[PDB]
Amino acid sequence: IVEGSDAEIGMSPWQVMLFRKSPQELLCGASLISDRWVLTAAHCLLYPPWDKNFTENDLLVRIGKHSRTRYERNIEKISMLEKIYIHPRYNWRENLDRDIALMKLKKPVAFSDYIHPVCLPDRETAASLLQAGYKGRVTGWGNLKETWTANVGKGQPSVLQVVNLPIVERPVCKDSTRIRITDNMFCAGYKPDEGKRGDACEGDSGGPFVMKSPFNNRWYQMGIVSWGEGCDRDGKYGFYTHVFRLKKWIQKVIDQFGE
Amino acid sequence: SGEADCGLRPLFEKKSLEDKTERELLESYIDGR
Amino acid sequence: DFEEIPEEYLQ
Ligand SMILES: COC(=O)[C@H](Cc1ccccc1)NC(=O)[C@@H](NC(=O)[C@H](Cc1ccccc1)NC(=O)CCCNC(=N)N)[C@H](C)O
Image 1: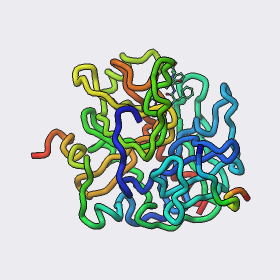
Image 2: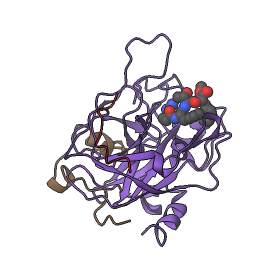
Image 3: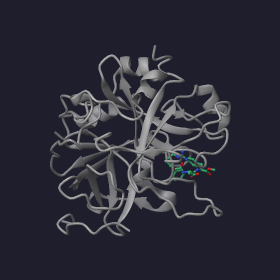
Image 4: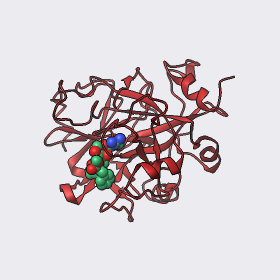
């Protein structure tokens, strides 16, 4: 998260951590949506051009975290996976279209002041909240800067970083990129007129992008952290997998399957 | 999706507390007033 | 790196 701010304890009890067993390392973000179902970008688990094709017995989900490196005992909770469901039409060759994946915990997770599920929107929440100009929030432990040869400081978060970013209008997203945009992917970030800055970044993929509904005081996941060109660069924005669009699939996989 | 009270944080919503930046979000919806 | 974790979380 570029130019973000440190979170607070229990500020996003749904942010999960994709942890690789060996080497031991931070894979990406995720989201507890049910006591036994987590959510993630498809590319954290699948990426032929880089040899990623993880199996469940190759990963760990750490919930309750806040510290990137420590091992917050009796606070966090580590869970093992039972199956990995990726979107059949996941398109890795050109633009990570349909960049979404569902993980099923070998066993259920209990809730505490730090482990709470996030809500998945409906057409009406999507309609009211998903609008150009409104602000959603992104949190994650990935890079603080875009890998630059000349940047001093070998930096990556001490603790869970958080940033609020506005939704931009689809035409603006499209004219900024030469990558083929798609209905299943939106963009956020300040525009060159605002002057400001902030962004998600390497390591942040798979992370939630939530919004709070003022009609019910409830947190809703509107997007998943996905891709971009560079991190925090001029006249550029970041892209999130439209969660509501692919929402039929999610539930298709969830309802009578892993219950 | 065993959730029942999703989106509700135990250390804020459930105890009626705000965070360092909530009102920013809630004010983006055109305006706070 | 990361603080080692309970070995059990590798079964
Ligand atoms: C100059 O940018 C580039 O060359 C390519 C453009 C690209 C995007 C999608 C698909 C193919 C190629 N960008 C990247 O690889 C960027 N990576 C990313 O954006 C990777 C996703 C990814 C993985 C593997 C391969 C490609 C893309 N995701 C992330 O960094 C998650 C946070 C959003 N990113 C952001 N705001 N920059 C990097 C930060 O610049």
